[PDB]
Image (spheres, coloured by chain):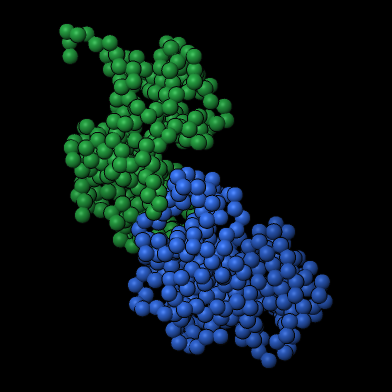
Chain colours: A blue, B green
Amino acid sequence: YYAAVDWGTSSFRLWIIGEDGAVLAERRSAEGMTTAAKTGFHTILDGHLAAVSAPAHLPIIICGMAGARQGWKEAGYIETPAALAEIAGRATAIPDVDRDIRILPGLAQRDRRHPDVMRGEETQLLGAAAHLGAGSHLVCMPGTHSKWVRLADDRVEGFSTFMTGELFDTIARHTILSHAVAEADTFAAGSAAFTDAVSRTRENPALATNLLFSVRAGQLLHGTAAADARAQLSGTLIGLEIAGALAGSGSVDGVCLVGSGGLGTLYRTALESQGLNVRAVDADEAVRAGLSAAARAIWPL
Amino acid sequence: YYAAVDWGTSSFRLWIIGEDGAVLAERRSAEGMTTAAKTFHTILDGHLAAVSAPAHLPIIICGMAGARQGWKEAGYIETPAALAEIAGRATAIPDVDRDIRILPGLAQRDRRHPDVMRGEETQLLGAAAHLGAGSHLVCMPGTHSKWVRLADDRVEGFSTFMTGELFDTIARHTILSHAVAEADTFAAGSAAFTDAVSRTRENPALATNLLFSVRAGQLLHGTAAADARAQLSGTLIGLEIAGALASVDGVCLVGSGGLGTLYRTALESQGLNVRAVDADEAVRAGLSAAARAIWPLAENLYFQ
């Protein structure tokens, strides 16, 4: 019996978990990191606990941006390489309250040639890894920042962020490419526009910023439909991510994909188009499971 | 004789020219094609009034004044294209008081590799003779950086890389604004810059990871804003060259000022010779060869 919270930058999810593992209650809102920093983390939380009649001494495990510098209380990082089990033990307690409330830290790769950082995904990893062996895994965690993580023996060995989602959104809205992709809201992951682009760039990463301009040139000279231009932009950026993810990885078979929604489908299509097997793990199921593994290790029954 | 106008996306430049060949006056500002579609004559009349231009001095204009989202759509001549075709394909802007033309751009129509250039073809009209003869490879940096295979007053093909526009939007609208924002500049020579260019030119695949690292670098160690900016610029540029190079010794850079330095710096570090050429000297020249061609002047039969 604990609450578990995924505190994101623009949203908030909470689950009350009973003694037997079952979800007894669930709450979900827009009060993410940026709202809570104006109006108060503790108050937003006390709101949801009251709304579902939590006991006053129900303990609470949190992951994500509630633990960033701009959040409720800095949770910091654990340096990789690091056993997945270190996470729960290095959680930060909220100091002047009558409830055990703890926030899990991010992971940091301090290497000077490859500095890298994650906050949130580590907890999804904790939930995902329970479904896999203790053997070797290359794990893809897509988003505004896709994380590619090397798991072995239940340790995170290292990881690489690729800013593909953030790049997509800036290129689509703030550059000339917006005149080619604005008219379209969606595209079909299954379309050739998409997987052709993933292949052009995966095979020719060096040309990336020529290929991006080609989406605009293509439109001007040949009337590329907005949906296909959107796909093309999308595919280019994700194919370049894949190229980087695999740049001397030996042979890799062999990828586990932690994702959900249309995002998860886009990536799976992308990865499978480049000849990789995919093992899907549902991103939301994995946070809860990650948050539950930590709770069971800090408050054992 | 003529007004020459180079009307870019973000900048306006004018030169008044005499039958002698000399510049007589000049105007600069930052009203480019995007600002101009706010106000399309008025900007042109203002600068003309300013410099005391004859009311019927004709006007030759290259650049984005000729795009769809501009003054009037000029065309494109498709590649390979003889540079000498350009002036003949110019497009009038109706005016009873003056003969105003805009130069077309070039288009590479290949369905793989579609590509487009509006203005750099006039810097190439300008510079073809000077550069020399036979095959050249010319790099033309800017918001959109052009790489052009030139031979005998002929563009054979070319490649845009959108490195400048990427630098800007990445610097202003992504998380990296936190890493670079409160710097405005960085010294081309700084090792932060050529390291970025080299690790990226060597590992194109990792580009969008490398970009994230400037911010993770700033979070974990405390990178100085100029070194971050440099890393940023360097990464983008290293990537361009990787792509441009996808043996040449062996390149001719056309550019001016800050960015010109930055690229020679970046290009030499990758082991290339850089025969440089001033950017504005090549445009004024390209607009001159067009002007002489449609409004040839009355010669003195006894001279040459």
Q: Is residue A217 at all visible to an observer of this figure?
A: yes
Q: Nearer the viewer, residue B50 or B188?
A: B50
Q: Tell me if residue B13 can be seen.
A: no
Q: Does residue A120 sit above or below B250 in this rendering?
A: below
How many badges with numbers are in the image?
Answer: 0
- In x, y percent, where is residue B77? 37, 37
Relative to A254, say whether B39 is above or below: above
* Quarter assignment of residue B204: bottom left
- The structure residue drawn at horizontal position 66% and vertical position 61%, both measured from the top left corner, is A10
* Vertical placement of residue B124 versus B44, above or below: below
- The residue at the point 22 percent across, 8 percent down is B300
Give how far across and how far down residue B122 sits, in percent. 34, 32
In what quadrant of the picture does the C terminus of chain A appear? Answer: bottom right
- In the rendered structure, the answer to whether residue B56 lies left or right of residue A285 reads left
- Left or right of residue B234, residue A27 in this image: right
The residue sitting at 34% across, 35% down in the picture is B121
Picture quarter with the N terminus of chain A: bottom right
> Which residue is nearer to you in this view: A285 or B213?
A285
At x 56% / y 70%, what residue is drawn?
A: A265
Relative image position of residue A289 (x, y in whole percent):
63, 81
In this view, which residue lies farthest toward the bottom? A301
Residue B304, given in percent of the width and then of the height, sits at: 17, 14
